[PDB]
Image (spheres, grey):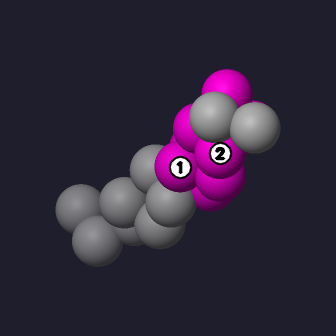
Amino acid sequence: AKKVFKRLEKLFSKIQNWK
C-alpha cells in the first residue's frame, strides 16, 4: 500500500544506531 510512511519512522531509529 501507500503506507510505507511507517518505514520512515523506522529510519529515524537507524539514526540512533549511528549516533
| Magenta span includes 19 | no
Spatial CA span between label 1 and label 2: 7 Å
Which image quarter: residue 17?
A: top right
Q: Is residue 8 left or right of residue 16?
A: left
Q: Residue furthest front?
A: 19
State the image coordinates of residue 13 (x, y, percent, origin top left): 68, 40
Q: Is residue 14 left or right of residue 4?
A: right
| Magenta span includes 12 | yes
Q: Residue furthest bottom?
A: 2
Residue plotted at (29% across, 71% down): 2
Q: As rendered, which of 12 and 6 lies closer to the eye?
A: 12
The kind of residue on which mark 2 rests is Ile
Assess disc 2: are there few (<14), some (14-19) or many (≥20) residues with their C-alpha within 10 Å of its C-alpha.
Answer: few
Tell me whether circle 1 and circle 2 mark residues in contact (CB < 8 Å).
yes
Q: As rendered, which of 11 and 15 lies closer to the eye?
A: 15
Name the quarter where the N terminus is drawn: bottom left
